[PDB]
Amino acid sequence: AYTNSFTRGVYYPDKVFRSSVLHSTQDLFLPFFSNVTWFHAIDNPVLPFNDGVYFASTEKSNIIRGWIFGTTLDSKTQSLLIVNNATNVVIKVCEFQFCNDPFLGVNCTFEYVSFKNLREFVFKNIDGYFKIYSKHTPINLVRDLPQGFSALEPLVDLPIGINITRFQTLLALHAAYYVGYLQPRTFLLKYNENGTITDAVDCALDPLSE
Amino acid sequence: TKCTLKSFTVEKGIYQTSNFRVQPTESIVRFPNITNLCPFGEVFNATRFASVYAWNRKRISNCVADYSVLYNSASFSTFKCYGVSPTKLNDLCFTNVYADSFVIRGDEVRQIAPGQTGNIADYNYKLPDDFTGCVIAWNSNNLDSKVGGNYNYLYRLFRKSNLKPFERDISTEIYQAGSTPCNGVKGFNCYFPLQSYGFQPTYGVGYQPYRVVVLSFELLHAPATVCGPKKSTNLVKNKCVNFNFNGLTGTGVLTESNKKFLPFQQFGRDIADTTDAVRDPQTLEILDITPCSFGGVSVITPGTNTSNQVAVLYQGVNCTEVNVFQTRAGCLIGAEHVNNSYECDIPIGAGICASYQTSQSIIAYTMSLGAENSVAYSNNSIAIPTNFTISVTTEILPVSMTKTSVDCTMYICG
Amino acid sequence: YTMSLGAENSVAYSNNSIAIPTNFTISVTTEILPVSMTKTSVDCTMYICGDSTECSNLLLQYGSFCTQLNRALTGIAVEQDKNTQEVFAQVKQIYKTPPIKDFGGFNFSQILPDPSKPSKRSFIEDLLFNKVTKFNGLTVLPPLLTDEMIAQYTSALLAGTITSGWTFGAGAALQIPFAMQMAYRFNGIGVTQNVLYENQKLIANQFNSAIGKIQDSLSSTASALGKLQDVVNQNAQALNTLVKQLSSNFGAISSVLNDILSRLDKVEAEVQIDRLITGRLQSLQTYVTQQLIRAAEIRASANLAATKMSECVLGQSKRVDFCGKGYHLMSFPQSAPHGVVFLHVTYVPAQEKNFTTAPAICHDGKAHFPREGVFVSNGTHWFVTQRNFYEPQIITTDNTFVSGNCDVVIGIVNNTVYDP
Amino acid sequence: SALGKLQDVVNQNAQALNTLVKQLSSNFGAISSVLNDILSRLDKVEAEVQIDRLITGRLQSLQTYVTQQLIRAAEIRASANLAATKMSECVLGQSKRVDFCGKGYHLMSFPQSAPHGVVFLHVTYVPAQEKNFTTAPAICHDGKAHFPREGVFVSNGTHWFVTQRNFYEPQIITTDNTFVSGNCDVVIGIVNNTVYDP
């Protein structure tokens, strides 16, 4: 099952204000208009991480609550954990094995806490500086992602140094969601007067985009 | 002017000489209040470090220190730096520091730098060749060696392939050194990948242990979690000043900002991508860097043969920033304005022209394009000239130049 | 596809026939030329060293490169005034328009100085000025002339050109009525002056209409400013490159000059800054070289414009495809950003008609010839006409001369040449 | 000061050579700009590096000089093309091109040599003494319209005359100096007058 990625998976490039500029960079990005896998909350498989990921979920009961990432995902060594515990957000790298089907029933070197509802995220590994970006909004559709622009906003950099080869999403249980991979791509951007990006081009998309 | 033109005599004209940058009025310093002491004392007096394949990436953050305690320290047998000089460390600010630290024999300490080779570099700790940081060590035969050999210290002697920059690997699996298919079994061409030093206190320097730290440095646009011991001033605005924010030196008008930032933006940047707006790290004040006014100094003069007097055009300047006369072209000091208009003489810009005249002074005026003339036109008017003249205008053209030649060889090499 | 070279046309050559036109057009053909680029200047020390005194000293190792860079951009900057002045300030006196427009039909109003507006721009010049689209040691100097002074010169040139013919370039503006002016331009291209008066109402209305069509062309056509907008874009593009070049490393550890100085010992920073200096210096020499070449290129267009001014405005050129296409009558300058626009006014024949011709005629058995023009017949009678308009005149004593007995000539014919 | 163009060319060459010389004093990051110092203080394996800086610097100054010379030579060549054209148009003939062979209606020109240049003395006409008159683009006589074979029709009030277009020289309108262009009706601003017949 698929949806099109459209121009989804765009995120803020650096911590710099610029005045309305048509700026450019090469970075890990979601390939424009790629088809990307569609999932039904009947299923939360283990997926590769590869270079980096886009994830998004279309919800109203908000069944999605987190992700687990790492080498083993069974906690036999460190494995990254993220869970939005409602008003708050847990992050850990724990070797403690939680439930072997990993849902909330309705030692760690790091441990911390901070269909209309589309929640969107982007994840990448850079020299063990693991960077994450985000957005969430109401939308008027279940089956496919919205075609309009927005640059996702930084959550964290995690310089934790884990070999994240695999990951899986996490739930609260007694929705639909979508996943795809980033690629090193040359890009063009459109800032505004308030230091804020407002459109972008994947140069690697086609000869016009070049 | 005389020095710009490298001569004691100068003709009538208008001449570049300098740019008057309105001077930086004071030197601001601003840093995060992160002034608790860094654990470098515990690092450089550590009880021990790890065996070198498992080198300690000890992140150092959220603190400050006087590095002169360290770079003048009698502790070190080795103290080296890359992309930085140690005298500057007390001015520096860093996003993070990482004290990549371990024990090895003295013969392998020379492997610990960019471009270096051998199994400690290649199978235990490989630097980026694009490093920024420092390499520090002390001979530890006093503490790490023991009689009968201290075998608690180890290194990777073998691996299938060399380490990438900052790669780390704890695997104990048998190294297949050749055609023997090891299948987890040691033997001929099937070896354990680690080796133990067995440090005896009687060993010579080549086998004597060394405690080692490599300070890997991170410097990026995010707030400086580390600095040297240097102390902030108060903040200042709306004046041309010298400044530092978060280790970044700069100079400009620290204007109040109409430039709305996003919350995560520590800086804003020019078309040049040079820093162009800044945040006070403590006061969280977004400052907009308007340039310090930088007037090109066009000196206006008759010739020194004629007169010693002068006028000055600071190009693009408003006179308040510095008798005087403002223009669209900038601030004209020392000329005398005139309501009349004549033909131009020294051209200045935006229709302004000047000359020196009689009580003598340099007048400045808007130029006259010429005599103005209403023609006697109609549907029936004519004029026809009853008399005429011959005339002899003289036209001058260059047609050649002096044929030079150079032996590039004898010119360069004599 | 293979491009068309145009549609083909086998012209029907013969030893015996001519096509001679019965009607024409007073079409107006626009032309555009650059005259100046933006007067930049770079303080090479400010650009290279950015107020690092350390760098500012170190640069003396490279000696007089920084002075000759200022000198070269100064030389360009000076000759921009020269270009702008030498195109427009060709007229010696600021002629001003008469209070009444008694031209004999020609509705100049759109290209004149606007007599109501506070600035002397024409209606068409306003469309042009409305069509067209730095902090780090780079600077832009002002033009010497103001944009309104430029309008006074184009106004004056146009006013002399209206009130006095071409005479105001070479003498006083000897006044003569504008209908007599057109009769001279006609008299130039072999069109006998009577032909103007014989068609004046129509001829003026063609001009008026053609002017209106140029307004609409410039109003509609976003590409019309192509040459002038190109010159602006190239110089903006060059500076934007020269600014972004500040950020190249040239093999230094950083392209931020202050950053090196904020990390390093002088003994290191000398080597690093030797790279940046050599880099920024090579980039600035590159820009200056391209500006010198582009300034020579603009100076060709400035000499070309100054000549188009000296010929097409201040006379009637004999040079085919110099003052617009075809049998040129007159031209008007209009100002623009960085450049100039010419309206060229030209007589173009349009309605052809075919005829029989003989290069000579025999009446006394001696050969007669056209004192000017061609011998022609439709087959009913023989006539002579001037070259570019079908005015059949009876072949007479009055429009011919004789050159001996007929024997040598070929295609010659018998005809009854009349004597009054 | 009239000869400023030629003196400027000489000054530009002199300025360029003096610059090219003076750059030999610059060290370009070498310990001395005198080549013999390095060769008399240092020894080959070290000496080469400083010598290579001097080579690089001296060479880049020479590259710059040659490049400015090419551009400057292109300007002089454009000026030589202009001169060659004025020689052919103005000296080997007379120019129809207004002001090209000097300002005014051109008569003739004389060349004179000068160092690195040429000068022309352009002999030109300029009109000098206006009289105003009234004018009409045609005459009507005997129900025929008349036009000048050459010249303009003018009046001092007291008389009407044909005259040549650029020097006042009046003559009476005659059947000889006029041509007829048909009946009287079509012309604007035409006037009644007698045209004489000899």
Image (cartoon, coloured by chain):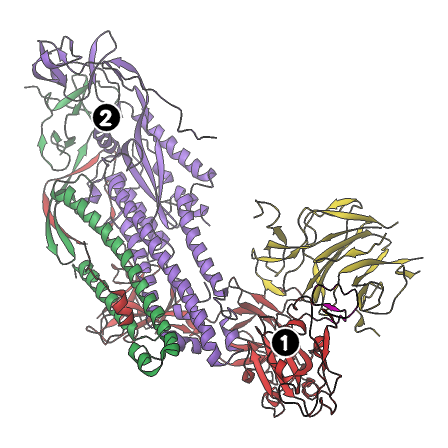
Chain colours: A yellow, B red, C purple, D green
- Where is A33 relative to B301, above or below? above
Along the line of sight, the residue nearer the viewer: D71 or B215: B215
State the image coordinates of residue C374 (x, y, percent, origin top left): 20, 19
Q: Do marks 2 and 1 both belong to one polypeptide chain?
A: no
Is residue D65 shown in magenta? no
- Give the residues drawn in magenta, as a range: B168-186
- Where is C226 relative to B221, above or below? above
Q: Quadrant of residue A87?
A: bottom right
In the rendered image, which quarter contains the C terminus of chain B?
bottom left
Amino acid found under the numbered disc labelled 1 = Ser
- Where is C8 relative to B407, above or below? above
Q: Position of B219 compared to A112: left or right?
A: left
- Where is C191 relative to C253, above or below? above
* Chain under callout 2: C
Q: Quadrant of residue C21?
A: top left
In the rendered image, which quarter contains the N terminus of chain B?
bottom left
Q: State if disc 1 and disc 2 touch (CB < 8 Å).
A: no
Which residue is labeled 1 in the image?
B216
State the image coordinates of residue D54 (x, y, percent, origin top left): 34, 72
Which residue is labeled 2 in the image?
C191
Residue C141 visible, this angle = no
- Secondary structure, magenta segment, majority class: loop
State the image coordinates of residue A154 (x, y, percent, origin top left): 70, 63
Q: Quadrant of residue D154?
A: top left
Query: Which residue is farthest front?
Result: B188
Residue shown at 94% from the left, 57% from the top:
A174
How far apart marks 2 and 1 lie (CA) works out to: 90 Å
Element on which disc 1 rests: strand
State the image coordinates of residue C85 (x, y, percent, origin top left): 29, 53
Q: Nearer the viewer, mark 2 or mark 1?
A: 1
Amino acid found under the numbered disc labelled 2 = Val
